[PDB]
Image (cartoon, rainbow, N blue to C red; front, side):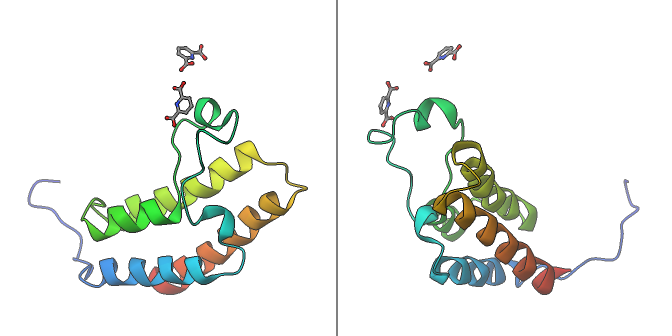
Length: 115
Ligand SMILES: O=C(O)c1cccc(C(=O)O)n1
Ligand SMILES: O=C(O)c1cccc(C(=O)O)n1
């Protein structure tokens, strides 16, 4: 509370580390469904069903232009990509399995980097 603070964690490398983790996700071979925004004009249903589209290139833009106030807001956008994937795709499909793989891949990098 006021004048009562926990020891300060050094957060000065967070931006560069998040950028590094995003790059590792983008080079994963199962990243292809997530690299660019879904085409809202060519994919029936997606615009109406998915209230908040997110993808790796949009995350890169936000990251590089200072639009994440902290670590956690970056993580939320990354998870949003995979939650959207799960909402719109059957588990038993290539894209469905891609999403599962990428989420697990991310959460490991995340844990290994910060926790
Ligand atoms: O690209 C878009 O934003 C889009 C595409 C198809 C329909 C609509 C719409 O009717 O709102 N919007
Ligand atoms: O964007 C739309 O098509 C829209 C607007 C208002 C309500 C609803 C709805 O009830 O789904 N959908």
